[PDB]
Length: 230
Length: 230
Length: 7
Length: 7
Ligand SMILES: *Cc1ccc(-n2c(-c3ccc(OCCO)cc3)nc3ccccc32)cc1Br
Ligand SMILES: *Cc1ccc(-n2c(-c3ccc(OCCO)cc3)nc3ccccc32)cc1Br
Image 1 (cartoon, rainbow over the protein chains, first blue to last red):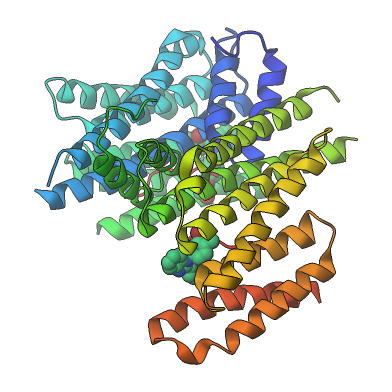
Image 2: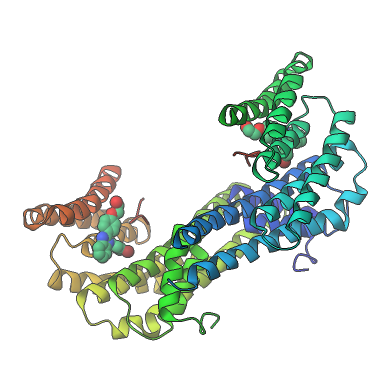
């Protein structure tokens, strides 16, 4: 709504300025405005959208975990629960906003593997964040929504992208985290990380120096998780 | 307004939770609500108010400096200026909010030296932040408002507080920064820091170990600035 | 556990 | 120049 009067190019320009200023709420609002212009996003623009919202929700999640820990230790008056609930509702609202952008209409217009995988990974991630705070009748459905998004992304990535593609790698990293932290499936998490790492290692020989650097950065995160989990 | 229905004690409790969660915007809103209950603030509460707003405006100022630097290098379309202006207006609004709390009615009800000095120091600081971004007809008046607040605080502190009092020290630190960065008076800045440091050093013998630690922490900041400035 | 970081 | 920090 509020960004409706600003040029798409100006919104993208201001998102980049907001990133430099570490103003991630502004960054996200600018990128939401850009998405709502109705055009497909380029690779760079997709990454600006992702950075903005991941920083916003990352702060919310960190706050939620602090407050949830205090609340758990408490089990005084209603204030800890109320404030945890306030942060939770704000986080849920941001996740619903991102999911709404993906559904209206980024995913449906995304035909190339790179864009479709990127958006489905995001869909998995934001349902995952919803799952982290879920306790009601729809919690299993939230978890399944994350799983379904990640699984569609995985199926396309395996068919259409090399094993070293950074999006394919990051998707596998995050789906492995889903398995370990949300689905109570540590063995699946470990298997996925290990297979991803090994298949990427075997394809590094095909890469330029710059691509190598990108792929190996994410492989190291896989390895770091495998080290933590084993 | 929005915190009008919450108990004062609950607002203070939630400000502390917000601090632990690094949710400083929430912290500031909670403390604004507490101030608006109309009662005087205790020492601890005064410090919660200060921490909350200093974190909020500190982020805004950092963003403003990033954007102002980009704008200066640019001198492309209006977007850098517009977004710098947007951050500036938000910063001005936060400063006006704090100044409004001080004027309605924290300062007038503050009779003890410790509270009155604390609030007048805050008044100087927030006019100082207004001065950092000021360019219009009232810029000299903004600078003088900062100066006047700091000077009243200094006069009370010198009469009523020992030279090692942390508020007296922090006031001198910030007034010295005012002189160096805003009033184009580096010699006054250096004199103030040096005299403050030396008079505090001579009074350290009177302190407990815990008071000593507090006073010396701020003395070291004075010394650090003197080292930078000379 | 760590997921993909932001830059 | 640095002013008084926040905790
Ligand atoms: C989910 C996702 C995966 C990959 C990329 N991405 C990267 C890239 C991201 C992070 C990296 O390491 C992090 C730890 O050091 C390494 C590479 N490079 C890309 C190029 C093109 C498109 C996407 C890319 C982004 C994201 Br959001
Ligand atoms: C403006 C102001 C001055 C002093 C205090 N303050 C302190 C205190 C603040 C910061 C310190 O060091 C910072 C660098 O390490 C050391 C001490 N201690 C206090 C006790 C009681 C009242 C105020 C106090 C706060 C502020 Br906002």
